[PDB]
Length: 326
DNA sequence: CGGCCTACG
DNA sequence: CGTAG
DNA sequence: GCCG
Ligand SMILES: [Mn+2]
Ligand SMILES: [Mn+2]
Ligand SMILES: [Mn+2]
Ligand SMILES: [Mn+2]
Ligand SMILES: [Mn+2]
Ligand SMILES: [Mn+2]
Ligand code: NA
Image 1 (cartoon, rainbow, N blue to C red):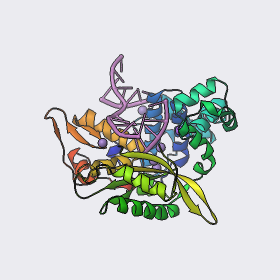
Image 2: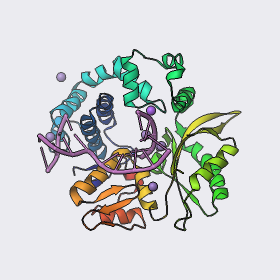
Image 3: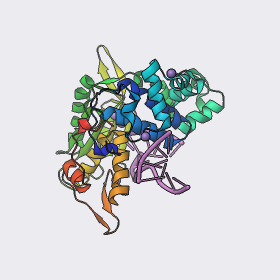
Image 4: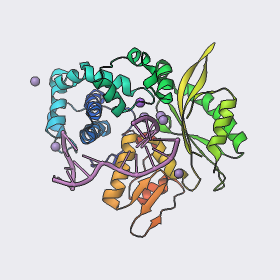
């Protein structure tokens, strides 16, 4: 088992679901306390289990696995022997965990804001609604739409949404294309939002595109909320039988020269991409982001025509999106 | 021990 | 500060 | 919390 998640296939469904979910609770809780290092170790340990070919049945099967030390091994041991880990359950029921989870779920609220509200004594959404002058416009939108935004987006919803985005994109710039990214591109059947990547085959034609797209979607009455720019974090009105629901949609524009890097970055998973950027820098001495791959010694950017090119540049076996579910 | 991804709005 | 994978 |  290699130490970096980008070095091994990780399928969407696997054989250690219960174990990985428990470690991800501890990862999430570490994030709420500002310990990004502990969050990373628990996320990485969970991801190792997702990549295994069969269920872990005995503690002995953890020896030699990367990111399993005393703490993560004790969690698994308690789950194997008792079906529950007391630490995990204590986190689950804790007021701190439940409230930080509730608050950070709000669009416009991060860990730092949620923690401040927690220290001020706030605990519920209605607490926040009874003091609305303290909220940003973004947070007000996130709170008004919170119920709809807590409802999973179905892959069945995504097709209809892509065609309306394509219509606006085609008026904004004929020939421009829309690609579904994020978790749906990795094969998820549900998600918390829809992610789209927009480009145009003629380099430079994409300049100034996203404002033109947003104006057109807004004129169609489809935009419930949005803030030159190249990323837009929106709330869209999506049809429903006899009504509609609010859905989070992210739109990103990239020049076609950067498209493989943007496709790779926006297809995720989040942990996969953090691990891939870490691997690039620490093992290969190259700097990766969603715009390109930089050699800081020769002062040059790698040209990529495909995701396959990027894996080759980095000396990694190619993984299709459905094996990037770290 | 230091490091932990790397951007844009 | 928020947001993205 | 774990790697290297
Ligand atoms: Mn170990
Ligand atoms: Mn026991
Ligand atoms: Mn998504
Ligand atoms: Mn998104
Ligand atoms: Mn850019
Ligand atoms: Mn996210
Ligand atoms: Na949030």
